[PDB]
Amino acid sequence: MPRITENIETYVTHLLSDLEPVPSQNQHLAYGYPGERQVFKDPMLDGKQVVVVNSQYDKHGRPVTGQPDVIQEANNYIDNLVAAAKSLIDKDKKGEKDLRKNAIDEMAKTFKKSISETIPSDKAKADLFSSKKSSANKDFLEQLAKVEGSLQQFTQAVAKASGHKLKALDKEGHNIRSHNRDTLIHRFKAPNSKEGEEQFIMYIPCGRYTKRQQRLMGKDESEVNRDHDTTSHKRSDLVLGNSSMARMIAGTRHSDGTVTIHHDSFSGPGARMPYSDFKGADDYKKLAIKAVTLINQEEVIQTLAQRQIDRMTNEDLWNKIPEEYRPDELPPDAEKARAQLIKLYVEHNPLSVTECYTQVVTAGQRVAAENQKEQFEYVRQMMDAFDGSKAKITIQTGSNTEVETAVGYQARMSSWGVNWFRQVGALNPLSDNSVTKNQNARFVNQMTDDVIRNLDKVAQNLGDYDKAGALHTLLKGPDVSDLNQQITEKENALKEVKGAYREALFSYFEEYQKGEGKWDQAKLDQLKNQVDGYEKSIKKQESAIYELHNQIDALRKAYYTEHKGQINKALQELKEQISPVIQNKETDPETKSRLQHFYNSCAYLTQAQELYYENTWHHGKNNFKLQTLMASLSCELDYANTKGSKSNNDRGQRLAQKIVGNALWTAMSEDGLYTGEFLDHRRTHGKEVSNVEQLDRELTTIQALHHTANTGVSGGKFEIQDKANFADNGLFGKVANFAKIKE
Ligand SMILES: CCCC(=O)OC[C@H](COP(=O)(O)O[C@H]1[C@H](O)[C@@H](O)[C@H](OP(=O)(O)O)[C@@H](OP(=O)(O)O)[C@H]1O)OC(=O)CCC
C-alpha cells in the first residue's frame, strides 16, 4: 500500500536482481507474450508485482521482442475484459452471478480457439522496422482486421451476457486496472555497452493521495497508506487524483550488479482535470473542474517532495541533520533508521520543489478539441496559483509513518503541440496558434534566467578554462533586468491574492461536492463570486506581466540572430578544450561532472534558442526537438520534469522516448557531452542502420507495457508526422485501437 520510502538507488538495485517468479493465476493483469513479458514479485513491497522484458534478437540483429502479435493482444483483450465483466457482475444488484460469469468464460474459451484456429501464427506478427506496405506487414494488417471483427463480436456478446453496457465495461476496466499497477522494466544492451554491462528503463508507479484528497473521496484521514494508480481514462465524475503517472528511471547495471542512474523524471501525469465533465457543463461546474485541477496540483507537489527525499542516501540525510539534533545512536533496523532520518531531515529543513511541465497537447486546436485548451489554461493557472508559495504536504517516512510539512513550490510550464495541428497555416481555421504564444514566451525567459543565474554561480569559480568564460559572456544575452525587476515586483504583488484565491477555491469545491439536494445556494453564490473577483483581478495582473515578457522576447530574439554564429563557435571551442580533460583518468570524478553540467546546460539552451527564435520547432523534421531539449535542460538544472498529453499514452510517450534516448545516448559517449546526434539523425528503417537507430529501436518496448497497464492492450497510436523521427513504423497503433472499439 505504501509508496517507496527507501532510497531510489537502492530500490532500483533490488529491482534488477533475481526476483521470485509469479504464476499466471496470480498476476493482477494479463500481459501476454509468455516468456517475453515475465512477471515477478516486487523485492520490497508485499503483493506488488513487476514486469520485465529482455531484448532478444534474430540472426540479423533485429529485435524479436517488443513486436505486435495479434493473437497475443487478442488474448489480452479477452482476458482483460473478462476481469472487468466479472468485477462488474460481482458488485451489481442482480442475481444469477455465477451463471453469468461461467458463461463469459465459455465464450472467452471459444473465442480464443476460434482465433488460434483461423489466424496463422506466422502472419500474426508485425515488423516495426520494415515498411507497413511490405508483404509481411500487409499480411499482419489482414489478420488484424479479421481479429478486430471478432473482438467486436466477443465484446458485443459479453455486454449482453453480463447485462452491462460497453461504456460501463470500459469504465470498470479503468477502475480495477488502476489499483495495483506493476513496475515496468526493460533491460537491454545499448550500442557500445561496455563488457558485461546492461542498460535499463523502468516506469515505477507513484500516485499517493494527499490529506485533502483523502477527506474528500470520503475515506479515512488517519491512513498513512493512500495508494492509487489512476489510469489515462479514469476522469469521469469529479474524480480526484493524477492519471497515468510514473517515475521514469534509466541507467546502466554494472557487472557487480550496482547501478548508475542516467535519467530520473516523471512520465505524466496526463490531464490534471477530469476532462469528461466539460460536456454541456455550466459555469458552476467549470469552476468545480478548476478546483479539482487545483486539488491535483497539490498532489503533484506532494509527489515531487517524496521524490526528493528518496533521491537522498542515508548519508545525505544525516549530513543535513544539524549536529546537535542527531540521536545518540541509530535504530538496529535498516527501515526504522531511515524513518527516523527522514523525520529529522524534514523537521529541520525548509523543503522546496521545482516542476517543469513540458506539455505536448495542442492548446489552440479547434476540431476534436477534446477540451485541449482548458488542459492548457487550467493547469497553467494553477501551477501558477501555487508558484512562490507553500503547500501542506505529507511525506511518507516508513510503511506506517508520515510527517507534515510546508513544501515551497516553483513552477515552469510550456506547451508546444506535437500533432498535425501543432502549427497551422496563416488564416487556417482549424486551430488558433497563439493560445500559448504568451506562456511559452514566458517559459523561455524563465528557463534562460535560471541558467544564467546558474552560470554566474559556477562561472565565477572554474576559470582555469577560459572559453567557458567567453561562452558565458555571450549567453548573458542583453541587459534586461530593468524589465526583469518590474516582473519580479509584480509577481510578488500577486502572491497574497493567489493564496486567498486558492482557499476560496478549496472552499467552493467543498460545498459543490454536496450536490444540488444538499447545496446551500447562498453560500455557493458567495463562494463563486469571491473566486471570480480574485480571478478577474489576477488575470488583469498576469496580463501586464506577459507584456514585459514579450518585451524581453523581442529583445532576446534580436540578440540571438546577431550572435548565433559566434555562440556556436564559442560552444564548439568549449567542447574542444573540455573533452580532453574529461577522458583523462587523473581528473577527479567531481570536477568532471561540473564540466559536463556546464557544457550540456549550455548546449541545450543554445539548441533550443535556435528552434524557438527561428520558429522552426514545428517543422516536421524537428517535431519533438524543442520540447525534449527543454525537458533535458530542466533535468540539467535539477528540476522535476513532468511531461505529457491528455491521457499520456500516445503523444506523452513519444516525448518520453526522445527524452530518455537522448539521455542514454549522451551518457554512454566517450565523453558525456550532448551532441544532438540522437535527435538529429534521420532514421532510415533500412536493414543496416546506425547506432542511434539501433538504440531508437529499443525504446518502444516500455511504451507498450505502459500502454497495456493503462488500457488492457499494447500500443501508443501517435500519428507520426515525419517518418525520419522514429525507428518504428506506427504499427502498435493498430492494436492500440482494440481499446477504442465501441458500438
Ligand atoms: C485520423 C483521425 C482524424 C481525427 O480524429 O482528428 C484529430 C486527430 C488529432 O490527433 P492527435 O492529437 O495526435 O491524437 C490524439 C487523439 O485524437 C485522441 O484520441 C487521444 O486521446 P485518447 O485516444 O487517449 O482518448 C490523444 O492521446 P494522448 O493524449 O496523446 O495519449 C491523441 O492520440 O487526428 C488527426 O490526425 C487529424 C489530422 C487531419
Image (cartoon, rainbow, N blue to C red):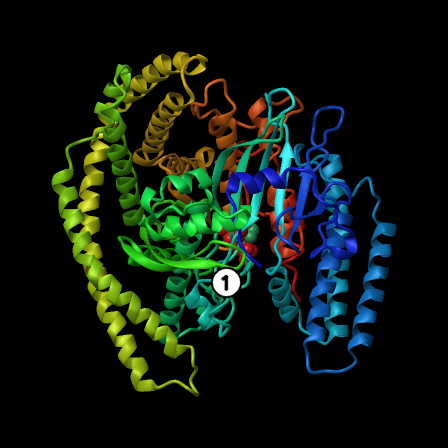
Residue 450 falls in which quadrant of the image? top left
Relative to residue 82, is residue 134 depicted above or below? above
Label 1 crowding class (10 Å Cα cut-off): few <14, some 14-19, many 20+? many
Between residues 709 and 263, which one lies in front from this camera angle? 263
For the point 27% across and 55% down, the residue is 389
Is residue 684 shown to the viewer in this render? no
- Is 130 situated left or right of 561 in this image? right
The residue type indicated by label 1 comes to Val
Between residues 171 and 395, which one lies in front from this camera angle? 395
For the point 32% across and 52% down, the residue is 409
- Is 56 situated left or right of 498 in this image? right
- Is 689 situated left or right of 599 in this image? right
Number of numbered discs = 1
Q: Residue 118 appears at what percent x and percent y?
A: 86, 51
Determine the secondary structure under disc 1.
loop
Q: Would you name the residue on which mark 1 appears? A: 224
Is residue 195 shown to the viewer in this render? yes
Q: Which residue lies furthest to the front in this view?
A: 328
Q: Residue 499 appears at what percent x and percent y?
A: 25, 63
Q: Residue 1 appears at what percent x and percent y?
A: 58, 59
Q: Residue 316 appears at what percent x and percent y?
A: 41, 39
Relative to residue 223, is residue 442 depicted above or below? above
Residue 570 falls in which quadrant of the image? top left
